[PDB]
Image: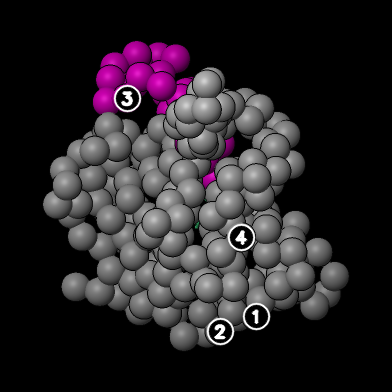
Amino acid sequence: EKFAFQAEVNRMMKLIINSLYKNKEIFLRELISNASDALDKIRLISLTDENALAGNEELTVKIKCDKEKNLLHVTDTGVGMTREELVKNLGTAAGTSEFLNKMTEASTSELIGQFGVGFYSAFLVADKVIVTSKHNNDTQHIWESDSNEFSVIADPRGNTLGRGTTITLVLKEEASDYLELDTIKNLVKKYSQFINFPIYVWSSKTGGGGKTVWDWELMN
Ligand SMILES: COC1=C2C[C@@H](C)C[C@H](OC)[C@H](O)[C@@H](C)/C=C(\C)[C@H](OC(N)=O)[C@@H](OC)/C=C\C=C(/C)C(=O)NC(=CC1=O)C2=O
Protein backbone atom coordinates (compact mmCIF):
# COMPACT_ATOMS: atom_id res chain seq x y z
CA GLU A 1 0.00 0.00 0.00
CA LYS A 2 2.62 2.53 1.13
CA PHE A 3 5.77 3.63 -0.71
CA ALA A 4 9.35 4.59 0.14
CA PHE A 5 11.31 7.47 -1.39
CA GLN A 6 14.39 6.81 -3.52
CA ALA A 7 17.41 6.25 -1.24
CA GLU A 8 19.84 8.73 -2.84
CA VAL A 9 17.17 11.31 -3.64
CA ASN A 10 15.98 11.35 -0.03
CA ARG A 11 19.53 11.71 1.35
CA MET A 12 20.31 14.60 -0.99
CA MET A 13 16.99 16.34 -0.32
CA LYS A 14 17.61 16.04 3.43
CA LEU A 15 20.80 18.07 2.98
CA ILE A 16 19.14 20.56 0.63
CA ILE A 17 16.21 21.18 2.94
CA ASN A 18 18.39 21.24 6.09
CA SER A 19 20.49 24.04 4.58
CA LEU A 20 17.43 26.29 4.96
CA TYR A 21 17.46 25.93 8.76
CA LYS A 22 18.29 29.62 9.33
CA ASN A 23 15.11 30.73 7.56
CA LYS A 24 12.57 27.95 8.11
CA GLU A 25 9.68 30.39 7.58
CA ILE A 26 10.21 30.07 3.83
CA PHE A 27 8.07 26.93 3.81
CA LEU A 28 5.03 29.22 3.87
CA ARG A 29 6.33 31.15 0.85
CA GLU A 30 6.61 27.86 -1.04
CA LEU A 31 3.15 26.56 -0.10
CA ILE A 32 1.59 29.90 -1.05
CA SER A 33 3.45 29.84 -4.39
CA ASN A 34 2.27 26.29 -5.03
CA ALA A 35 -1.33 27.28 -4.27
CA SER A 36 -0.96 30.24 -6.64
CA ASP A 37 0.19 27.91 -9.44
CA ALA A 38 -2.71 25.50 -8.86
CA LEU A 39 -5.13 28.45 -8.88
CA ASP A 40 -3.63 29.93 -12.07
CA LYS A 41 -4.14 26.56 -13.73
CA ILE A 42 -7.81 26.17 -12.83
CA ARG A 43 -8.42 29.84 -13.69
CA LEU A 44 -6.97 29.32 -17.19
CA ILE A 45 -9.04 26.16 -17.61
CA SER A 46 -12.21 27.99 -16.51
CA LEU A 47 -11.83 30.62 -19.24
CA THR A 48 -12.96 28.10 -21.87
CA ASP A 49 -14.70 25.58 -19.58
CA GLU A 50 -16.87 27.32 -17.01
CA ASN A 51 -18.15 24.00 -15.64
CA ALA A 52 -14.57 23.59 -14.41
CA LEU A 53 -15.41 25.57 -11.27
CA ALA A 54 -18.65 23.69 -10.48
CA GLY A 55 -17.20 21.78 -7.51
CA ASN A 56 -16.23 25.01 -5.69
CA GLU A 57 -16.99 28.39 -7.31
CA GLU A 58 -14.28 30.37 -5.48
CA LEU A 59 -10.56 30.93 -6.19
CA THR A 60 -8.87 31.45 -2.85
CA VAL A 61 -6.11 30.48 -0.46
CA LYS A 62 -7.30 29.93 3.11
CA ILE A 63 -4.97 29.27 6.04
CA LYS A 64 -6.05 27.86 9.39
CA CYS A 65 -4.04 27.49 12.60
CA ASP A 66 -5.48 24.66 14.68
CA LYS A 67 -3.78 25.16 18.04
CA GLU A 68 -6.04 22.53 19.60
CA LYS A 69 -4.60 19.81 17.35
CA ASN A 70 -1.16 21.28 16.68
CA LEU A 71 -1.88 21.54 12.95
CA LEU A 72 -1.40 24.24 10.31
CA HIS A 73 -3.62 24.02 7.20
CA VAL A 74 -3.03 25.74 3.84
CA THR A 75 -5.98 25.24 1.48
CA ASP A 76 -6.51 26.39 -2.10
CA THR A 77 -9.37 25.91 -4.51
CA GLY A 78 -6.98 25.45 -7.39
CA VAL A 79 -7.02 22.59 -9.91
CA GLY A 80 -6.23 19.83 -7.41
CA MET A 81 -4.47 16.50 -8.05
CA THR A 82 -5.70 13.00 -8.94
CA ARG A 83 -4.64 9.93 -6.97
CA GLU A 84 -2.06 9.08 -9.65
CA GLU A 85 -0.53 12.55 -9.54
CA LEU A 86 -0.18 12.34 -5.76
CA VAL A 87 1.63 9.00 -6.08
CA LYS A 88 3.71 10.07 -9.07
CA ASN A 89 4.51 13.72 -8.31
CA LEU A 90 4.98 13.34 -4.56
CA GLY A 91 7.02 10.16 -4.69
CA THR A 92 9.46 10.41 -7.59
CA ALA A 93 16.33 10.43 -12.48
CA ALA A 94 19.85 11.65 -13.22
CA GLY A 95 18.35 15.11 -12.84
CA THR A 96 19.77 15.17 -9.33
CA SER A 97 23.11 15.90 -10.99
CA GLU A 98 21.66 19.07 -12.49
CA PHE A 99 20.61 20.04 -8.96
CA LEU A 100 23.96 19.51 -7.22
CA ASN A 101 25.71 21.18 -10.15
CA LYS A 102 23.55 24.17 -9.30
CA MET A 103 24.48 23.59 -5.66
CA THR A 104 28.24 23.00 -5.71
CA GLU A 105 29.01 24.67 -9.05
CA ALA A 106 27.31 27.90 -7.95
CA SER A 107 21.09 30.30 -3.02
CA THR A 108 19.32 27.09 -1.95
CA SER A 109 16.35 29.22 -0.93
CA GLU A 110 15.98 30.28 -4.57
CA LEU A 111 16.95 26.95 -6.13
CA ILE A 112 14.28 24.74 -4.58
CA GLY A 113 11.52 26.73 -6.22
CA GLN A 114 13.19 26.59 -9.63
CA PHE A 115 13.87 22.85 -9.33
CA GLY A 116 10.29 22.13 -8.30
CA VAL A 117 11.00 20.72 -4.83
CA GLY A 118 9.94 23.68 -2.71
CA PHE A 119 7.08 21.64 -1.27
CA TYR A 120 9.53 19.65 0.85
CA SER A 121 10.58 22.75 2.79
CA ALA A 122 7.44 22.02 4.82
CA PHE A 123 9.49 19.37 6.62
CA LEU A 124 11.58 22.14 8.21
CA VAL A 125 8.73 22.85 10.61
CA ALA A 126 6.72 19.61 10.42
CA ASP A 127 7.32 16.00 11.48
CA LYS A 128 4.53 14.91 9.13
CA VAL A 129 2.90 16.44 6.07
CA ILE A 130 -0.54 15.43 4.79
CA VAL A 131 -1.87 16.42 1.38
CA THR A 132 -5.61 16.17 0.81
CA SER A 133 -6.68 16.79 -2.78
CA LYS A 134 -9.70 16.76 -5.07
CA HIS A 135 -9.41 17.14 -8.84
CA ASN A 136 -12.45 17.32 -11.15
CA ASN A 137 -11.42 14.02 -12.78
CA ASP A 138 -11.10 11.94 -9.59
CA THR A 139 -12.43 11.45 -6.06
CA GLN A 140 -10.80 13.06 -3.00
CA HIS A 141 -7.58 11.37 -1.80
CA ILE A 142 -5.06 11.78 1.02
CA TRP A 143 -1.25 11.55 0.79
CA GLU A 144 0.74 11.32 4.05
CA SER A 145 4.47 11.23 4.79
CA ASP A 146 7.03 11.49 7.59
CA SER A 147 9.69 12.45 5.00
CA ASN A 148 10.91 8.86 4.64
CA GLU A 149 7.87 6.85 3.52
CA PHE A 150 4.43 7.78 2.22
CA SER A 151 1.04 6.28 1.43
CA VAL A 152 -2.09 7.35 -0.42
CA ILE A 153 -5.69 6.49 0.44
CA ALA A 154 -9.17 7.41 -0.73
CA ASP A 155 -10.56 10.04 1.66
CA PRO A 156 -13.24 8.34 3.82
CA ARG A 157 -14.80 11.76 4.42
CA GLY A 158 -15.72 11.92 0.74
CA ASN A 159 -15.43 15.05 -1.38
CA THR A 160 -15.26 17.75 1.29
CA LEU A 161 -12.93 20.12 -0.57
CA GLY A 162 -15.17 20.39 -3.63
CA ARG A 163 -12.01 21.01 -5.67
CA GLY A 164 -8.51 21.94 -4.57
CA THR A 165 -5.83 20.98 -2.09
CA THR A 166 -5.11 21.20 1.63
CA ILE A 167 -1.54 20.95 2.90
CA THR A 168 -1.68 19.90 6.57
CA LEU A 169 1.42 20.25 8.75
CA VAL A 170 1.90 18.35 12.01
CA LEU A 171 4.22 20.92 13.58
CA LYS A 172 7.45 20.04 15.38
CA GLU A 173 7.44 21.05 19.05
CA GLU A 174 10.02 23.72 18.23
CA ALA A 175 7.68 25.25 15.63
CA SER A 176 4.68 25.95 17.84
CA ASP A 177 5.01 29.66 17.00
CA TYR A 178 3.44 28.97 13.60
CA LEU A 179 0.14 28.33 15.37
CA GLU A 180 0.03 31.95 16.53
CA LEU A 181 -2.22 34.17 14.41
CA ASP A 182 0.10 37.19 14.59
CA THR A 183 3.09 35.21 13.34
CA ILE A 184 1.11 33.60 10.51
CA LYS A 185 -0.51 36.88 9.45
CA ASN A 186 2.89 38.58 9.33
CA LEU A 187 4.39 35.83 7.18
CA VAL A 188 1.42 35.66 4.80
CA LYS A 189 1.66 39.40 4.16
CA LYS A 190 5.41 39.14 3.63
CA TYR A 191 4.91 36.39 1.03
CA SER A 192 1.65 37.44 -0.67
CA GLN A 193 3.46 39.74 -3.12
CA PHE A 194 2.64 38.58 -6.66
CA ILE A 195 -0.16 36.15 -5.85
CA ASN A 196 -3.16 37.22 -7.92
CA PHE A 197 -5.69 35.54 -5.64
CA PRO A 198 -7.03 36.57 -2.23
CA ILE A 199 -5.37 34.87 0.75
CA TYR A 200 -7.19 34.59 4.07
CA VAL A 201 -6.27 33.50 7.58
CA TRP A 202 -9.04 32.13 9.82
CA SER A 203 -8.80 34.46 12.80
CA SER A 204 -10.46 35.87 15.87
CA LYS A 205 -11.86 39.36 15.24
CA THR A 206 -13.21 42.05 17.54
CA GLY A 207 -16.97 41.52 17.55
CA GLY A 208 -18.05 44.48 19.64
CA GLY A 209 -19.19 44.86 23.23
CA GLY A 210 -16.54 42.42 24.42
CA LYS A 211 -17.61 39.70 22.00
CA THR A 212 -15.10 37.64 20.06
CA VAL A 213 -16.01 36.37 16.59
CA TRP A 214 -14.20 34.20 14.07
CA ASP A 215 -14.01 34.68 10.32
CA TRP A 216 -11.69 34.73 7.32
CA GLU A 217 -9.39 37.75 7.34
CA LEU A 218 -8.08 39.05 4.01
CA MET A 219 -4.28 39.46 4.00
CA ASN A 220 -3.64 40.88 0.52
C1 LIG B 1 4.66 23.71 -11.82
O1 LIG B 1 3.96 22.99 -10.80
C2 LIG B 1 4.76 22.72 -9.73
C3 LIG B 1 5.44 21.50 -9.67
C4 LIG B 1 5.28 20.45 -10.77
C5 LIG B 1 4.08 19.54 -10.52
C6 LIG B 1 4.38 18.50 -9.44
C7 LIG B 1 2.77 20.34 -10.62
C8 LIG B 1 1.56 19.47 -10.28
O2 LIG B 1 1.54 18.34 -11.16
C9 LIG B 1 0.72 17.29 -10.64
C10 LIG B 1 0.27 20.29 -10.44
O3 LIG B 1 0.14 20.71 -11.79
C11 LIG B 1 0.22 21.51 -9.52
C12 LIG B 1 -1.00 22.38 -9.84
C13 LIG B 1 0.13 21.09 -8.05
C14 LIG B 1 0.78 21.79 -7.03
C15 LIG B 1 1.65 23.01 -7.33
C16 LIG B 1 0.62 21.29 -5.59
O4 LIG B 1 0.27 22.38 -4.73
C17 LIG B 1 -1.06 22.69 -4.73
N1 LIG B 1 -1.45 23.70 -3.95
O5 LIG B 1 -1.84 22.06 -5.45
C18 LIG B 1 1.90 20.66 -5.05
O6 LIG B 1 1.57 20.06 -3.79
C19 LIG B 1 2.72 19.91 -2.96
C20 LIG B 1 2.43 19.64 -6.07
C21 LIG B 1 3.81 19.07 -5.73
C22 LIG B 1 4.81 20.04 -5.65
C23 LIG B 1 6.18 19.81 -5.73
C24 LIG B 1 6.70 18.38 -5.93
C25 LIG B 1 7.19 20.95 -5.61
O7 LIG B 1 8.03 20.90 -4.72
N2 LIG B 1 7.15 21.97 -6.47
C26 LIG B 1 6.31 22.16 -7.50
C27 LIG B 1 5.62 23.36 -7.57
C28 LIG B 1 4.85 23.64 -8.70
O8 LIG B 1 4.24 24.71 -8.78
C29 LIG B 1 6.23 21.25 -8.54
O9 LIG B 1 6.89 20.21 -8.49
The answer to which of marks 2 and 4 sits earlier in the sequence is: 2
Q: Are marks 1 and 2 in contact (CB under 8 Å)?
A: yes
Neighbour tally class for label 2: few under 14, some 14-19, many 20 plus, Cα within 10 Å: few
**Viewer-proximal residue among 102 and 113:** 113
Q: Are marks 1 and 3 in contact (CB under 8 Å)?
A: no
Q: Quadrant of residue 193?
A: top right
**Disc number placed over residue 56 in the picture, else none:** 3
Could you say where residue 172 lies in the image, as x and y percent from the top left?
Answer: 52, 71
Q: Secondary structure at mark 2?
A: helix
Q: CA distance from mark 3 to mark 2?
A: 39 Å
Depth check, mark 1 against mark 4: the one in front is 4
Residue at position x 54%, y 55% in the image: 179
Residue type marked 4: Asp
Q: CA distance from mark 1 to mark 4?
A: 24 Å
Q: Which residue is mark 2?
A: 11
Residue type marked 3: Asn
**Residue 69 horizontal side relative to residue 41, left or right:** left
**Disc number placed over residue 157 in the picture, else none:** none
Q: Which residue is mark 4?
A: 177
**What stretch of residues is rendered in magenta?**
34-62
Q: Quick check: is 39 in the magenta stretch?
A: yes
Residue type marked 1: Leu
The answer to which of marks 1 and 4 sits earlier in the sequence is: 1
**Residue 79 horizontal side relative to residue 12, left or right:** left
The answer to which of marks 3 and 2 sits earlier in the sequence is: 2
Q: CA distance from mark 2 to mark 4?
A: 28 Å
- Residue 95 can be seen in this image: no
Principal SS element in the magenta part? helix
Depth check, mark 1 against mark 3: the one in front is 3
Could you say where residue 11 lies in the image, as x and y percent from the top left?
Answer: 56, 84
